[PDB]
Amino acid sequence: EERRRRAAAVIEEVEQRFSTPTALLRGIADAMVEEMERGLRADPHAPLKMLISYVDNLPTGDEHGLFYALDLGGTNFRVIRVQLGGREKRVVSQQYEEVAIPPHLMVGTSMELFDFIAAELESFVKTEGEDFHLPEGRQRELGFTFSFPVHQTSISSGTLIKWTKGFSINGTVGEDVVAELSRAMERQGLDMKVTALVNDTVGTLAGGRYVDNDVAAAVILGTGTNAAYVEHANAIPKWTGLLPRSGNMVINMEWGNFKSERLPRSDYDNALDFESLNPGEQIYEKMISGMYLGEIVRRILLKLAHDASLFGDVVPTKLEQRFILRTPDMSAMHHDTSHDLKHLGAKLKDILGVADTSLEARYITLHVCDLVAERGARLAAAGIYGILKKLGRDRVPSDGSQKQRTVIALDGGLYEHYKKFRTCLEATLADLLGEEAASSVVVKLANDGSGIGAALLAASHSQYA
Ligand SMILES: OC[C@H]1O[C@@H](O)[C@H](O)[C@@H](O)[C@@H]1O
Image (cartoon, rainbow, N blue to C red; front, side, top):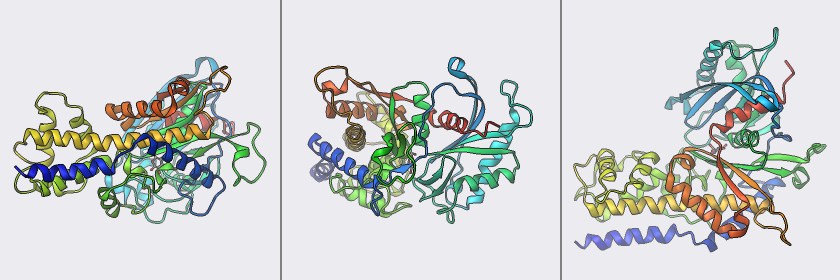
């Protein structure tokens, strides 16, 4: 019908506003570096907070002993327990338990949340355990990974800046999250001391360098997105005090808050933000991260349903319901290669509650996913490139000459389980780099990286008991 061109008009503006020509990506990468410097001198209201992590020395390998970690993410939390054995034996025993965070605890009271966590820890610690031992008369020490922006005050203390993703708990901003976790643990009451507080990007970069000494930065691409890297302490103007022996400092960029007029946004992006739980915050992250991609697709699919009767002559009711299309569902449809888009069709039936779908409609749906997933992955690649620019690792020496080896640790369901996203990410990154510098850059999955990473940092910062 003539619908067909009204539908093409919509898809045309999507392609047009989501366009990321590499020329635009280089400009975005330059913008990201400018913001990393604005954040490092603590310019007022800089988008990138560039938070000093108090981690001046990353894991070496010569850590030994029994140490726990608590890993609080946007969707789940883990209770980890490792037994380290030096540079030779490394991780001798590992035990972990992962729990999904009940949705109400992302938006209730802080006591409700930390009591829920602490109680899962208390009962996990009692499953210990013949393989892990702690000298007699000692306290167990814990690494705390906190996947939200924290203004740090010591390796083990820090204030909450704001929540992100789907969390919004009153009365917790400004408070010390380790103190909040410790009272929960005494209400439990377990004798445990938190010796390291780290963001999940900072923890992933620790866990990553424990296995590969070439890790210079870690990027999370999961339910949220953020990045951390190793900066030279003498490159941080906002720094006060003695610099560290090592001369380095791991910076939590908090790059989801990146905003820039160069970012290719659309009305679907403004609508998502206007109805988000944190309006105006984390602009960049809402173009990239797993909490948001599926909802961008739903909002594009809904305009087509209405302006092009794409799914019938009445709009399916479920398609008007926010967050009904998650990002894993998007990923399942996007990877269907059956001649008639049979699986993508089955998902649309469940998600929209229709009985059947056209086959033109499924190709448009699949094209809508491709437009959304690829603007997110190309932009994430521009960010990684910016980090490399800031490390002077977008260039290759010079004479020629030994090339460096620079590893990036990645974690998150987007990078780990969304295959076209990861591919587009790495091809764009390689293409921003050059066949040359590219050969020196490694991108690794650093699974469950944040927790052992926190556990290891909690160790090098023990009270020796
Ligand atoms: O979950 C990964 C990232 O998501 C961001 O929204 C959080 O604010 C970061 O602290 C975290 O590193």
